[PDB]
Amino acid sequence: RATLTVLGSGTSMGVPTIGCDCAVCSSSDPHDRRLRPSVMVQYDGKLVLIDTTPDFREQALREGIKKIDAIVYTHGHADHILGLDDVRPLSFPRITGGARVPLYANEKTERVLKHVFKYIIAQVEMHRVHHEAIELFGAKFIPVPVIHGETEIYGYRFGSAAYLTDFSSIPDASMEMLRGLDILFLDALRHKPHPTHSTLDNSVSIAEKLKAKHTYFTHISHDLPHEETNRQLPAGIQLAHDGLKLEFELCLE
Amino acid sequence: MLMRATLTVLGSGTSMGVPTIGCDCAVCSSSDPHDRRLRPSVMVQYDGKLVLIDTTPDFREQALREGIKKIDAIVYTHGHADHILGLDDVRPLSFPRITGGARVPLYANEKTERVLKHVFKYIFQVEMHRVHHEAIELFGAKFIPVPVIHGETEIYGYRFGSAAYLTDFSSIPDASMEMLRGLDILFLDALRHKPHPTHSTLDNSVSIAEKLKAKHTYFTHISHDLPHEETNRQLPAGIQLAHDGLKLEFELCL
Ligand SMILES: [Mn+2]
Ligand SMILES: [Mn+2]
Ligand SMILES: [Mn+2]
Ligand SMILES: [Mn+2]
Ligand SMILES: [Zn+2]
Ligand SMILES: [Zn+2]
Image 1: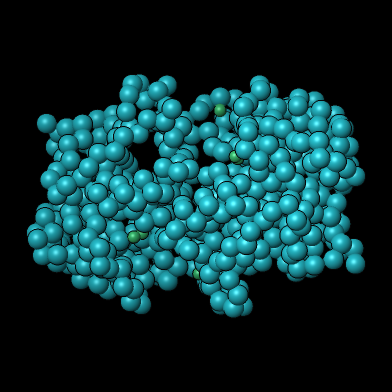
Image 2: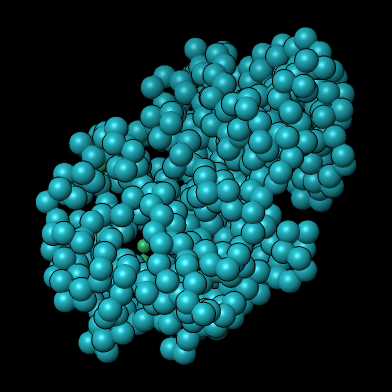
């Protein structure tokens, strides 16, 4: 029924990181090339975007996105929001219908979006996300609280899939919201500790507790070579890559 | 102390770039590489130094493309989004490891500074320097601010040695026209064919070009209204649309 597409699998500065001479930043492996982190979900002629990274224009062009039905935000950090400016051409009435391009965010994220963009017609409209499910064209997108260093942000569960980026930990109550998945995306930044993200080993431990059929890591930095890392991971656990497409089930009402 | 300098076009396109997302017109569908245009920016290299003019939302791609490993100074024309949003992506070049210890200096007029500090309040690695009408002394070279009018807002272009870079203008004051004579290289805004409230048309910028008589004039900030090769085939000798990746040699005192 539904399709998830990885628009970017990379960390906040992407892979390569500008100015870096490390082997991964010079890789001949295309999978080591990673735009900033975002996915899109398509179902029933609809397109739902999670986060608008600074690479949004390139992401949209290379996937031939010509219309967006809804945008949902995990949080307000620059690698997740700075592409909102480039969404504008698709918010024009000729494309929209119609009509509207709804943006869903919690109060913190909304405040950030307003500060960053209300100084610098494009009809977007802000909708508030609370802990209750978001109703999008028949589907329910359930906000899943996760801890991003100190700050609580959201990942999202939708049908048999879930997407959780930018976390250092996941509270027990949220772990219980993530059982029985077909597809699971988790933050996995690198091996060395980072206060607001999760290590590869940490995220493997999490994956082994949640037991999704397939688990994919994202927000990946230059510390994780794609091939080297994947041949060390368990059977149902892998690093995502840019362009990865996955099919799954989702119930519409 | 005249030395060889190189100007590189990092992006030759308008604010939404070429192609425009969602558009299926002839130019957006073009397979001519020069019809692919990132947001507008150039860099200037001389004496082992690199000076960047504007930080577009495409800055990461532009830097990777050109193998930029260090930025010695950044100079801003104005504060519109297509000229500033890439500052976030300047951060990995601003750490002591790469810089050598000093912050990356940014140069901007007061209105542009105001917008940068507001938008990138989380950033303020980098240090702000105020530009007025006096020349900017950068590593021996002088970058002269050239006032231009962007609708009704005054912004800056810059002249440096025998080159000048002027984007996002609808008009150029007389006093500024007088600053722009005898160039080897001149960049001018040319958005599209039809008059626009804040930009210059192809025809208008050709008229300006023929008044200023630079050896070579290049147009930038180009929209999908202008096919690259077909337009260049029709322009006067010495006048052409720029393209992403264009490199030009010129001279610079000190
Ligand atoms: Mn992030
Ligand atoms: Mn974050
Ligand atoms: Mn512009
Ligand atoms: Mn402008
Ligand atoms: Zn690296
Ligand atoms: Zn077009």
